[PDB]
Image (tube, rainbow over all chains, first blue to last red; front, side, top):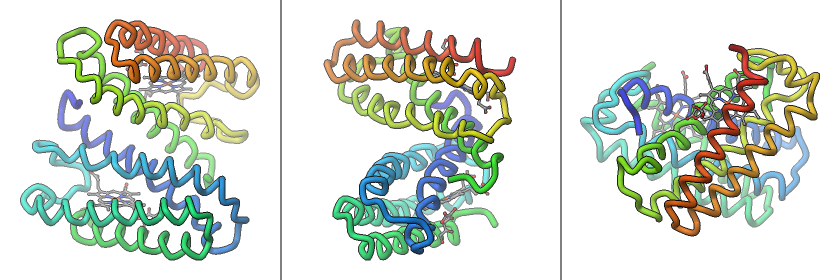
Length: 126
Length: 126
Ligand code: HEC
Ligand code: HEC
Ligand SMILES: O=C1O[C@H]([C@@H](O)CO)C(O)=C1O
Ligand SMILES: O=C1O[C@H]([C@@H](O)CO)C(O)=C1O
């Protein structure tokens, strides 16, 4: 859907800004510093689920740029596995949010966060 | 969810970048220049539906900036009505996509586009 490669870079950077806000806005809730409203978090995690699928289609072939390391394209199977791990962790976070269980939420949230950091450590320019 | 007002501006600009890409990538389909796959468009419009709700919460009180006109906050009822119109047009686009009807899709897509332009004409700095 991108007229030029720069358009894919702009799209993915926007997508990761959104996904990051929908993840990180739950930090105070997971830490107990903000109240836990199960419905609020269920709805938010549904948004995060949709957003979490979007960046990956904007690393198509030819969209080299931004802070994406080139190893994203040359180790395509290894990058796909960091992305799949992250998405399966998002499924576990959805399950926790749907269950309305703060303990389960905290654990799943930590797993998600670890998966974000693991991909950045390998595939995001420093 | 924004530590500072600048964070709301960054979020909404990212949100409108995503929503714009998910809307505008359907232009070739509506024009017949790309094939119409009803399932493909149904899925895409589900993403657009989620995205289309996101910008509006990032014009909270105090988030003046970017290319948002100040009349967004001082004519809050009038801005809310441009946003509601746009969201009700998104509902009609969802219905068309769910029905798998290209004629209905084209008509709904045009209504959505008009609603985007009408809000920009009033509320987006030139
Ligand atoms: C690979 C499988 C990743 C996962 C999982 C996550 N992120 Fe990511 N992120 C990745 C790349 C390759 C890039 C660079 C994109 C580009 O083209 O520039 C990013 C970027 C971000 C950014 C922007 C940082 C900046 O300097 O602007 C943020 C804020 C970010 N990523 C956050 C984030 C979060 C919160 C994730 C889990 C919830 C997450 N990322 C996962 C690769 C990958
Ligand atoms: C008000 C009810 C709006 C509707 C409906 C739509 N848009 Fe919008 N848009 C609006 C504002 C107030 C702004 C500025 C945001 C800021 O703080 O800067 C925008 C911005 C955009 C942009 C970015 C333009 C730029 O110069 O970067 C785009 C690409 C954009 N809007 C597209 C868009 C589309 C495709 C819409 C319908 C599908 C749409 N907008 C609706 C206000 C409103
Ligand atoms: O909200 C965020 O969480 C991850 C990471 O900090 C988790 O360790 C990340 O990159 C963000 O922007
Ligand atoms: O894709 C887009 O459609 C609207 C408008 O051009 C429709 O008239 C807009 O602002 C876009 O970025």
